[PDB]
Length: 276
Length: 269
Ligand SMILES: CCCS(=O)(=O)Nc1ccc(F)c(C(=O)Nc2cnc3nc[nH]c3c2)c1F
Ligand SMILES: CCCS(=O)(=O)Nc1ccc(F)c(C(=O)Nc2cnc3nc[nH]c3c2)c1F
Image (cartoon, each protein chain N blue to C red):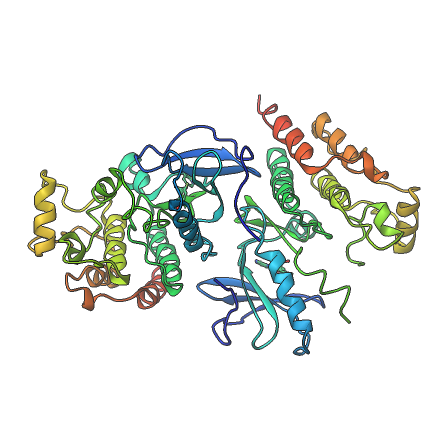
């Protein structure tokens, strides 16, 4: 039944995930596996019971667009091993190497993302940090949804990690999240808005607000709704129905935002109306 | 926690998968899904508790080379829904359409298969019917291991299209449990022999009884002088090693995977 991977089965190799909360390594375990070690310097029960529950959230997922949970580790460190995806990550493509994606693909990458999210939700999971850097293009045509694990084990734990990954990701925070209004700003629609920003990523190939150099104002304005994405950049050939759906996903007023089933539906349809 | 898919979420469409053991349909459930319905005309407890346990075997698996278990169904029929793989199936490629695979790939397809099997085993699962028709090439470059589910729900419920991959000690039903890791290896051997030759073994003997008789008496084995010219000597050697009539002389998968991972990084120059 259970997924705990014993000490020394996983062969931790080349390093790649650099952050402060955990560290991602390419590894080997019945073949190529990614492994993220939480570098929490060994628990410390029952922090340990709280990590097991977060794994519980993970294995609730079995979908071809959610990243595949493979097993976890308590022995040398804490960790999570997931499949290894050969190929980069939407962010890297759009913003590091500046891949020119054909439009048919872009819509495709939107769908899959939408596909997966619809799933994450259907099973009561809120991602809490969708963004192009957690969307991985595997073998360049499949989408795997990324860094949604844990969270419960981040707002109750000590480190500079709820000051980093609340930071490197603000561009995708819907307003009602930016200004920490209360306890739970996060919600399906929180997730949608982010989906909206990746949409705006795909369709423009830039990150929003590339001309404002102080990252405080971005925060101030976005949450006060003085600032929003410049929807006059969806590249010429961006289908009107999409640009429309994007703008729909990005509503400052979280209640005017579509949930994902409807979002997926309007993408599955605008697709079958193009190649002619 | 649980995977039971309620009635009428799955949209069963175009038909494809033939036979008893199950009939397979392309479907839709959070996107494209394959579904196999057991057409057992509704249980009949507690046959039903015995199908749930077979699913239990399935969800023990989470690997990028084992086919992805997605959820099961008790409502309209019994069923299992798995991911939908776009593209064919090793058997179809090699023997129906006759794909010319570049050798670097062939070895790759061997590895992945070996990759997945090593996994199936590590977690105490015996496949009991590896064969090119349960190896699916998804998007043509990834390998998903196939029809290993159930089995406990097949020998207790009311062997042919797959004999070519049966190690001898299995063919002649010697006793109760002929099946074992090495049983599986021999089959892996035959897919190897498939990849490396592009034919099914014994293509010149037209009575399917003798195949059975001889193979199990060890009078007949695969014609290893067919591994196409450029088949690396180290592989042809490993194949022959995987195919030993004496099940104890067969390598387990870790070693098998190891000798494939190595003969790979020694070729492109
Ligand atoms: C659904 C996965 C469980 S998660 O903790 O939410 N996510 C989670 C957990 C552990 C990881 F290593 C990762 C991850 O970044 N994996 C990962 C996968 N393939 C890669 N190819 C290059 N770099 C990679 C990283 C992950 F995204
Ligand atoms: C018996 C338990 C389920 S399993 O053995 O793990 N998997 C399993 C079992 C039975 C099937 F027919 C299938 C199956 O046909 N899957 C399948 C998946 N994608 C396909 N694209 C075209 N044809 C396909 C078939 C399967 F993937």
